[PDB]
RNA sequence: AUAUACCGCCAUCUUAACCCUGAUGAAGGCUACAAAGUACGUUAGGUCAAGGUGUAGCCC
């Protein structure tokens, strides 16, 4: 949601451009166009910090996994 | 004599594209503590005094 409590225009724009979307959807949000909605609290700093930590860890681990798989493939 | 011959000079008057919204209607698109917007003619004009080119008049 944007600062007038309406959906972020980027949701509809990404749907138009066929870009998958992951999203934290609170009880007052619209999850219809988010490809992978995640119901949860988006206001408390603890929840937002947890979301950031989880996503950062997942992305970093995925990139490291790709690099080590490529290294193993090159070695073998 | 003629600018009521022309110039020279003064003066008069006329006169692109793109992207979104509306159910893809005419149509619309902004908020910064940001909410779709970005890329010349005219005149029986004057002036031959600090300028010129012609044209006609008269020649017991
Ligand atoms: Mg909320
Ligand atoms: Mg005159």
Image: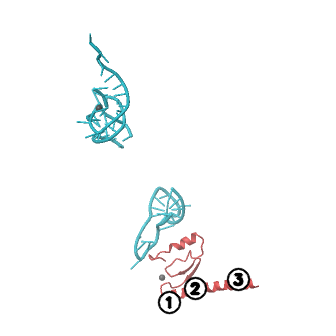
| SS of the residue under disc 2 | helix
Please rate how many residues cluster around mark 1, counting C-alpha atoms within 10 Å: few if below 14, some from 14 to 19, many from 20.
few
- Where residue A56 is drawn, which disc sits there? 2
N-term mark: 3 or 1: 1
User: Which residue is most to the bottom?
Assistant: A46
- A22 left or right of B47? right
The chain in cyan: B
N-term mark: 3 or 2: 2
Whole-Å distance between the Cαs marked 1 and 2?
A: 15 Å
Q: Which residue is mark 1?
A: A46
Cβ at disc 3 under 8 Å from ligand 1 = no
Q: Colour of chain A?
A: red
Task: Check chain identity for marks 3 and 1: say if they share one.
Answer: yes
| SS of the residue under disc 3 | helix
Residue B47: give x, y in percent of width and height.
26, 35
* Image-quadrant location for residue B41: top left
User: Which residue is most to the right?
Assistant: A76
Task: Check chain identity for marks 1 and 2: say if they share one.
Answer: yes
Q: Residue at x 55, y 88 (%)?
A: A53
Q: Which residue is mark 3?
A: A70
**In the depicted view, which residue is nearer to us: B2 or A45?**
B2
Q: Residue at x 58, y 70 (%)?
A: A17
Whole-Å distance between the Cαs marked 3 and 2?
A: 21 Å
**In the depicted view, which residue is nearer to us: B15 or A53?**
B15
Q: Given the image, what chain letter belongs to the residue carrying mark 1?
A: A
Q: Quadrant of the C terminus of chain A?
A: bottom right
Residue A74: give x, y in percent of width and height.
74, 83
Please rate how many residues cluster around mark 2, counting C-alpha atoms within 10 Å: few if below 14, some from 14 to 19, many from 20.
few
Is A4 above or below relative to B45? below
* Image-quadrant location for residue A52: bottom right
């Amino acid at each position: 949601l944007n600062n007038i409590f309406e959906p972020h225009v980027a949701v509809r724009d990404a749907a138009k451009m066929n870009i998958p979307t992951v999203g934290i959807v609170d009880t007052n949000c619209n999850p219809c166009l988010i490809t992978y909605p995640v119901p949860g609290n988006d206001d408390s700093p603890l929840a937002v910090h947890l979301y950031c930590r989880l996503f950062q860890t997942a992305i970093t681990r995925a990139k490291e996994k790709r690099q080590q798989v490529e290294a193993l493939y090159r070695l073998q």
